[PDB]
Image (cartoon, coloured by chain):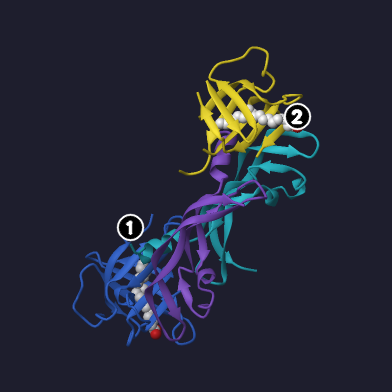
Chain colours: A purple, B cyan, C yellow, D blue
Amino acid sequence: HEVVKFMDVYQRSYCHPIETLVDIFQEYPDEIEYIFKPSCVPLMRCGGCCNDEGLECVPTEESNITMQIMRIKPHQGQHIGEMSFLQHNKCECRP
Amino acid sequence: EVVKFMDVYQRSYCHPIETLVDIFQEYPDEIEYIFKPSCVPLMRCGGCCNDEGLECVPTEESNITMQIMRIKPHQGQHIGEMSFLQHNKCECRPKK
Amino acid sequence: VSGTWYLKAMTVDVGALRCLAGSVIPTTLTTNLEAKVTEVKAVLSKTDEPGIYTAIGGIHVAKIGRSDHYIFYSEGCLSGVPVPGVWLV
Amino acid sequence: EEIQDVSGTWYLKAMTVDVGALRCLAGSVIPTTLTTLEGGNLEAKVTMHIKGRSQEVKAVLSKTDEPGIYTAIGGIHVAKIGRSHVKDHYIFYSEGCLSGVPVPGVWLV
Ligand SMILES: CCC/C=C/C[C@H]1C[C@H]1CCCCCCCCCC(=O)O
Ligand SMILES: CCC/C=C/C[C@H]1C[C@H]1CCCCCCCCCC(=O)O
């Protein structure tokens, strides 16, 4: 359409879980000596806006998801292993 | 159930993804306004190039126009159409 | 409650207002439609009220949140320049 | 126009580097050359860097497994990185990479 109308913009931006591509080191910050492939993963996380400085968008339901990641210890060995990550399923704007 | 390696890799590789961006980041000289909503969904390059020497950046951009409530200090408010930049295509290229 | 509603009556001073909008969780929503939000009451219909809220225009209402949170704006908000209004939060 | 049907499962028939202790062969590559051989086998040349400076390795891959010298490596799974637009950028890994523990391997960059 020519323009995204106001209520559609509001609905699409308002606090909800959204696919976010997150660096594996952000979730496993002490595993910085490994190289991972891929180096980031797609995780549903609360995002968007609550449009009121009195409120933050925060999770109310979370789940864990396991993904196969190539974990490389350089000059040592490598393998695809399972890594667990936290996702968000439901969010709300809270004080 | 477990996400298989090739699926994770294909899903995470550098490409344009809907990203929620604060309008004040796009319109930093308009930080005296209040906008509702305060953030908008824009397709932006995201994900990984799986090589610390490469970065995921846009190769093609476009404009999208969105109705936003614009609350002007001491002058009232209205819905106004605001244009925003989107990424249509991305590449993995050298950092620096 | 989504759709266009036209204002029949509300417990508010329109004054110079042309742009009515906000984001609200109503206390009540009975039957026309009365809405109660703290307190403010308002009644609305799918039908018009000649020459009384006419500057404010129809009220467009949509539900927000993924499965009683509504956002709304008045037709009078649809101006190329800022107009007198309020944002009800 | 390019060689089609490279994505899928393939088995190593021959390779020009010693893959000794190796169990996990993987990488993300634009092949230097890819050739369809008479019979539907594929030959790949990839230009990499063994134990120092940079060399080109050839492999011949088949849709049929030969119970042979590459058994520890396992079947090679190949997929086009579809978000690398169109063309000839592939990701692959071998079955021997599926292990609870690190195993000897290479990642081609
Ligand atoms: C389902 C939700 C429908 C909501 C309808 C509420 C609309 C009827 C509007 C509510 C009116 C409140 C106006 C506040 C009073 C204006 C004066 C404020 C000021 O400028 O001083
Ligand atoms: C189009 C398919 C892309 C390639 C798929 C597999 C072909 C690359 C052949 C398979 C593995 C590549 C050779 C591995 C190099 C081993 C290096 C070991 C060493 O020199 O120490």
Q: Chain of mark 1?
A: D
Tag 2: residue type? Pro
Q: Quadrant of the N terminus of chain A?
A: top right
User: What residue sits right under mark 2 in the picture?
Assistant: C84
How far across and how far down the image is residue B26, in percent?
68, 49
Apparent side of residue B64 relative to residue D44 in the rendered image (left or right): right
Query: Which residue is found at the position 44% from the left and 78% from the top?
Result: A72
User: What residue sits right under mark 1 in the picture?
Assistant: D4
Relative vertical location of residue A5 with respect to residue B4 in this rendering, above or below: above
Q: Compute the Cα span from label 2 to label 1.
A: 63 Å
Query: Which residue is found at the position 54% from the left and 39% from the top?
Result: C69
Query: Which residue is found at the position 52% from the left and 53% from the top?
Result: B16
Apparent side of residue D36 relative to residue C3 in the rendered image (left or right): left
- On residue C35, the disc is none
Residue D1, quarter of the rendered image: bottom left
Q: Is mark 2 within 8 Å of ligand 1?
A: yes
Residue D44 at least partly seen: no
How far across and how far down the image is residue D54, in percent?
47, 81
Front residue of B36 and A55: A55
Dot 1: within a 10 Å radius of its alpha carbon, few (fewer than 14), some, or many (20 or more) residues?
few
Given the current orientation, which residue lies at the most extreme top position?
Answer: C50
Q: Secondary structure at mark 1?
A: loop
How far across and how far down the image is residue C32, in percent?
52, 20
Relative vertical location of residue D109 with respect to residue B34 in this rendering, above or below: below
Dot 2: within a 10 Å radius of its alpha carbon, few (fewer than 14), some, or many (20 or more) residues?
some
Tag 1: residue type? Gln
Given the current orientation, which residue lies at the most extreme right position?
Answer: B74
